[PDB]
Image: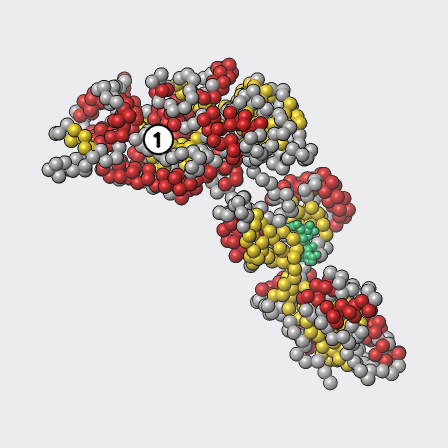
Amino acid sequence: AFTVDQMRSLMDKVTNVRNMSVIAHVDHGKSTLTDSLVQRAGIISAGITIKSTAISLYSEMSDEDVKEIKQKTDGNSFLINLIDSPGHVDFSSEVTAALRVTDGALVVVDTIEGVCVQTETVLRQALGERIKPVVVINKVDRALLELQVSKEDLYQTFARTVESVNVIVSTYADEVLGDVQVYPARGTVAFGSGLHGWAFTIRQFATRYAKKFGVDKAKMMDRLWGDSFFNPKTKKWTNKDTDAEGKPLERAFNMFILDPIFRLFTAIMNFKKDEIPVLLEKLEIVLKGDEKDLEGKALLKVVMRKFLPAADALLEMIVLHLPSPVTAQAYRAEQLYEGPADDANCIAIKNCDPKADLMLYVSKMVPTSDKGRFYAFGRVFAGTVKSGQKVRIQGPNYVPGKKDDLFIKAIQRVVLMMGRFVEPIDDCPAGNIIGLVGIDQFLLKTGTLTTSETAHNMKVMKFSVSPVVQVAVEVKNANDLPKLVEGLKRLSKSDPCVLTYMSESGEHIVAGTGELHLEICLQDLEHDHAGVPLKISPPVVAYRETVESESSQTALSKSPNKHNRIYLKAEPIDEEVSLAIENGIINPRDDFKARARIMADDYGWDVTDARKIWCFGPDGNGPNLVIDQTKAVQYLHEIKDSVVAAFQWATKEGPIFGEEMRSVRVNILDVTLHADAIHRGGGQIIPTMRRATYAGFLLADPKIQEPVFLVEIQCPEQAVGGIYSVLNKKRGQVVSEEQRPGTPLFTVKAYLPVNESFGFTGELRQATGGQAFPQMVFDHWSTLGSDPLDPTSKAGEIVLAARKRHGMKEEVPGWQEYYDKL
Ligand SMILES: CO[C@@H]1[C@@H](C)O[C@@H](OC[C@@]23C[C@@H]4[C@H](C)CC[C@H]4[C@@]4(C=O)C[C@@H]2C=C(C(C)C)[C@@]34C(=O)O)[C@@H](O)[C@@]12OC(=O)[C@H](CCCCCCCC(=O)O)O2
Ligand SMILES: Nc1nc2c(ncn2[C@@H]2O[C@H](COP(=O)(O)OP(=O)(O)O)[C@@H](O)[C@H]2O)c(=O)[nH]1
């Protein structure tokens, strides 16, 4: 327990500060180990509550051991900050940002299950941020009490684990740090049981056995591990697992360390009453009061704790081997700064200089009971933040040349994040971890607070600023529609990042930056902007009705007089052309000379068609045509207006299910009209044309076309695999994967069926730890090979569902009901 003054004092000596976190796979013991640490070293102040993000630990070392510290030191006291980052192990972004404020890690590894997958994934992440590790093989009790392991066996398991780790380390750690591998002999690997409350390091033993009988420790600890043996008989040290007579010799580690431990377990767990007292007498393990009447487990726990207090071993490695802000910021400053390595600020970070311009990294915002408020949490890398001081909050985006929506505000208060409690402080010098009240609105998630103008931003998580999620929105009571329409306009004004629009299928669509963004946009819309009961739903997809080939036989249809008859056929127009029609290159409003040249010379159509085309449909200019290939027909030109209108009709709503036609060309092969106008007017022709087209259409191997998005995702070469996994489950098709010379992030491009997209952006982030950054756009129509008229096929399923939704007959009228024989 300390006072704000006491605390502030600890903060001045940043050489004696340790910023770290416990890295561990699930269930390996991280929670219990940290509590172990908190119970002995945890710090308190001597009602606002917050979500614990970090804890302060206090540890004082001996004048001697303090000399074992190969790094600038000042005093015997140390302030250790145990940062906490346990959510979604996969989400590398979320994690990395958090690990970024630490300089060291206590890597935990189970004795039995050793180094595994989740383990090396976090260890590799750490190395990524240039963090130095130390290991603790935990749950050693498990190996004994359960597996009945033998001394040489256990040693082997440890050696194995230690070796595995180092592979990960050397194979990935930067050379700019020097061999950062872990060595049991050098005291950077601990062994113990977090649960039972005991652990040890080679150093602890070597040091003890180093004064009991004056002998140097450095030398001694090198022997207490590896292939060094001590022949009891010869009274000498050997490097041979066999003596002169070739006879077996016991390893130093097993002889002087493991053995004492193994004996204590046997003598206790076997209730050997007589040996216990003496065994304890030789190890100098003194028990008090009632403790002398414990048995088995209950006694073993008490003894081991008194013998090898787990805290001491862990605290030792942290103080003697994990770097101080000073030591680390020197070789970590590069990566932490987006700007030039010679910049003023980048150099301050290098120097953990408190007198410089502020370089404060906001790691994340944290929820408090201070009424919806969030205190900013992070590290002061350069300069010193002060309560009141004005600061330049620099968002994820910001750049020194653009007002870029910066934010120059005043730190309402600087505070210590003591677990669930905060304590007001005046200022805080570089190298410390700290919390800030008053930046709730100006920033969300990562950020940077500088006091300089040339000051660039520090390496923070990047954002998603493209519309990647959307839903259709409808009012529940028809009469509120105008309120929804007005609300949608309001929503947009108040939010530069929201997008609203009308779907081809007449729906109000609202798209957001990510799921959460969308969620609030909807809440805001329903209860504020429009204030009306809404109905959110997956938007309805539009399809196109087309033909795969020409009518298998002339389509014939007689008017309701039986007087007039149309013989036509249909065939598929080419995509290139439909596209030209659609993009306005082949336009109905252009002079004929222009249109004629284009279709004949650039799109290779017969030079005589352009003059026979009667119209484009639907709406006069759609990618569908009526070419008059008749001949001796007398009054052929008297019905033109009717045929055109009938065409504008059939193309707006095809026969498969009322969707627009696309790429359809109808050839009016022949017509046998009447002689008098009385029996050929509108009412008689339209019905014949319309009907005959449907007949032609249906007879031309009809098909449906589905809309398809073009999606572009930028993501880390590692997570790039998730992109593929999701896309495979959604009929997606990869178009290209292009590398970036410096591996800052590959960019994958692929086609994703629109009807295969609801929830995609969400699934993408899940399969990539939010590492992938998508953006998508409508790109093209694509014919489905399946048969639209067979309810079982993908297409038939679609049509079925559609007709159903529409309240149409579920069955699709075959061509015959449109065809007219004899
Ligand atoms: C500039 O905004 C664009 C916006 C105006 O139009 C969008 O495409 C809309 C389209 C546009 C085309 C053409 C007009 C012809 C056929 C229609 C469609 C019919 O089904 C096919 C498309 C999807 C529709 C609906 C299902 C919503 C469409 C429609 O009916 O309008 C995209 O082109 C747009 O670009 C963006 O960047 C954000 C992307 C939103 C992506 C949502 C992805 C969903 C993933 C998830 O929810 O997980 O939106
Ligand atoms: N036998 C044994 N069990 C342990 C030890 N440390 C933790 N456990 C148990 O392992 C499980 C997971 O531990 P916990 O610390 O919550 O794991 P974490 O998910 O890594 O934080 C719990 O049931 C613990 O009680 C240990 O040293 N020995």
Q: Name the residue under label 1.
A: 188
**Is residue 167 placed above or below 608 in the rendered structure?**
above
- Is residue 654 visible in the rendered image? The answer is no
Q: Residue at x 63, y 58 (%)?
A: 708
> Relative to the observer, which residue lies in front, 551 or 588?
588
Foreground residue among 326 and 436: 326
* Disc 1, SS: loop
Rendered-image quadrant of the C terminus: bottom right
The quarter of the picture where residue 751 lies is bottom right
Report whether 783 appears left or right of 423. Answer: right
User: In this orientation, does residue 339 appear?
Assistant: yes
Could you say where residue 503 lies in the image, as x and y percent from the top left?
Answer: 70, 54
- Residue type highlighted by circle 1: Thr
Of 432 and 59, nearer the camera is 432
211 over 103 or under it: above or below: above
Q: Residue at x 38, y 24 (%)?
A: 70
Q: Tell which residue pokes out farthest to the left in this image.
A: 245
At x 76%, y 65%, the residue is 586
Residue 367: name its quadrant.
top right
Image color mode: secondary structure
Residue nearer the viewer, 413 or 174:
174
Determine whether 261 is above or below 557 in the image: above
Residue in the image at 59% along x and 24% along y: 357
Q: Position of residue 89 (x, y in %)?
A: 47, 40
Q: Position of residue 410 (x, y in %)?
A: 65, 23
User: Horizontal placement of 769 versus 488: left or right?
Assistant: left
Answer few, some or many: residues within 10 Å of disc 1's Cα (few below 14, many 20 plus, some between 14 and 19). many
The mark tally for this picture is 1
| Dot 1 beta carbon under 8 Å from ligand 2 | no
Q: Position of residue 3 (x, y in %)?
A: 49, 15
In what quadrant of the picture does the N terminus appear? top left
